[PDB]
Every structure is written in C-alpha cells, then in structure tokens.
Amino acid sequence: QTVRIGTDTTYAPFSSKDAKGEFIGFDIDLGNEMCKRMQVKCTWVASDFDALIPSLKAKKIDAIISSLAITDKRQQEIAFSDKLYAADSRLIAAKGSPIQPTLESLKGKHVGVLQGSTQEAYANDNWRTKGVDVVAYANQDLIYSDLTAGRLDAALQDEVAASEGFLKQPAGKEYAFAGPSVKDKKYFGDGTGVGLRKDDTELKAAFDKALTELRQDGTYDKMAKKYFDFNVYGD
Ligand SMILES: NC(=[NH2+])NCCC[C@H](N)C(=O)O
C-alpha cells in the first residue's frame, strides 16, 4: 500500500530533522532505499520514541525505523527485520569527568535516559533502584540540553548517536564518553531492525529482501559512508 514508517527524529545521525523539517539520517536513507526496492510508497511519521511500539500495535504506523534495538522483550510484542546495524550503549559526561558507568561512580548523580529505551530499562534496573537519580526524558534533545545546562551529570544512549550526533558537534565540544561501552546482552539487544506487527509476514519478507539486496550490491556501504568511517553494521 503506502507503508507508514514511524521514527523519532531526535537521534542524529540516524534520525533527525534538517532546518526545513525534512527527515534526515541513516535510518531515513535505509528506509527510503528499502521502500524503493520494495516498490512501495513510504510515509514517514514522527513521534516520541516511547510512542512507536504502541502506535505500531494500534496500526497508526506499519513499521518502525528508529534505531530500534532487537531485544528479547520486544520480540514478545512485535516482529523485526534482519539487523540494520549494531548499537552499543555508552555514557557521556563533561570532559575531564571521572564518571564511570558504575553504581559507585553514579550513586547520587543525575543521569539522563530516553523514555522507552533500552538505556532506560538498564538504568532503571541497575541504577535507579540503588540510588542513582535516573531521569527519563520524552526525547534525546532534552537530554543533551539538560546535560549542557549542567542539570545532568551524565547521559546514557546509543554510542554512535552520542558520538556523531553530539560529541563531534559544536554543542558537545566540552563533553566526552565516560568509560567504555556498556555491554549487557540482557538489555541492549542484537543491533537494530525494522519493527513490524507479528502478523505482517509479507511486509517483513519484503523489507528483509530489500535489505539483503542493498547490502549485497554495496549500496549499504555507500550510504553508510556518508555518516561513518567505521563498520556500523557489526558482525
Ligand atoms: N530514534 C531514537 N530516539 N532511537 C532510540 C533508540 C535507543 C535504543 N537503541 C533502543 O532501542 O531503545
């Protein structure tokens, strides 16, 4: 039909808006390229990240492309395409900060996470319970803003989003990663994928076919090179 694809546009370089409100980023490029090969029209629909799976279940959108990690919990509720790219999580803080992604370091500190994210799940279970002030936000822009305002000591999000979308931008010049990637298979998933209703077998097959084809002919790498000088796909 027309495939309606939901995304949250506060996660550069994967999904954001340009100065005239056009959606831009690697998620947008992947979605548009897949749609072309599937020979379908696609309409992008912006929403808060935590609204994406509910909107999909409610049939207000037909697909999610929004750095949506493929997790065990989410697969109980929806289906996923094959992996679009890998996504590790990592903390950021002010440059020179001693902060580490540990309870010892973070107890009593204010740590921002995106509401509805794997980072929120991780932080709520491991940090909020034990006395870290975990603050959950409607979108990632509010997090970066509250961090630069000094209201947050740190923020947890996807590593590549933080790096390319903030640290390497003027806004994040005085900030840096605090500690290494936070690796936990119980939480952050096995890369990201197109989120789909479980019964939409045909639509999943179509996305999967287009994805294989655009990876195979080198289009994936061509598009990825616009944003990344490393292997974003992973293994
Ligand atoms: N467009 C976005 N805001 N994406 C947030 C993704 C965060 C994390 N990868 C998750 O799946 O929960």
Image (cartoon, rainbow, N blue to C red):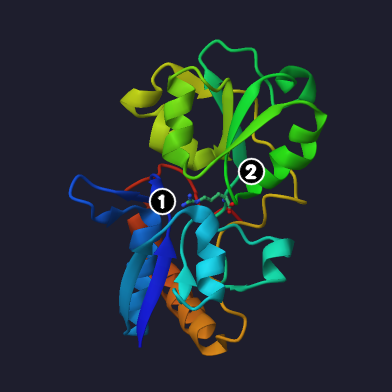
Query: How many dots with numbers?
Result: 2
229 up-or-down from 1: above or below: above
Front one among 164 and 115: 115
The image shows residue 71, relative to residue 194, as above or below, that is above
| Mark 1 residue type | Phe
Q: Quadrant of residue 182?
A: top right
Q: Mark 2 points at which residue?
A: 119
Q: Where does residue 181 sit, x and y in percent of width and height? A: 64, 35
Say whether residue 84 is visible: no
Q: Position of residue 72 (x, y in %)?
A: 73, 63
Q: Could you tell me residue 160's position as x and y percent?
A: 49, 41
- The kind of secondary structure element at disc 1 is loop
- Which quadrant: the C terminus? bottom right
Is 49 left, or right, of 126 in this rendering? left
Identify the mark at residue 14; answer none if there is no mark: 1
- Does the residue tagged 2 have its C-beta within 8 Å of any atom of ligand 1? yes
The reply, left or right, for residue 206 in relation to residue 134 is: left
Mark 1 to mark 2 CA distance (whole Å) = 17 Å
At label 2, counting other C-alpha atoms closer than 10 Å, the crowd grade (few under 14, some 14-19, many 20 or more) is many
At mark 2, the secondary structure is helix
Say which residue appears at 34% left-offset and 67% top-offset.
44
Percent position of residue 190, x then y: 66, 57
Whether residue 78 is visible, yes or no, is yes
Bin the neighbour count of mark 1 within 10 Å (Cα to Cα): few under 14, some 14-19, many 20 and up.
many
In which quarter of the view is residue 218 placed? bottom left
Looking at numbered disc 2 in the image, what kind of residue is underneath it? Answer: Gln
Residue in the picture at 23% in, 55% down: 22
Q: Earlier in the sequence, mark 1 or mark 2?
A: 1
In the rendered image, which quarter contains the N terminus? bottom left
Along the line of sight, the residue nearer the viewer: 172 or 127:
127
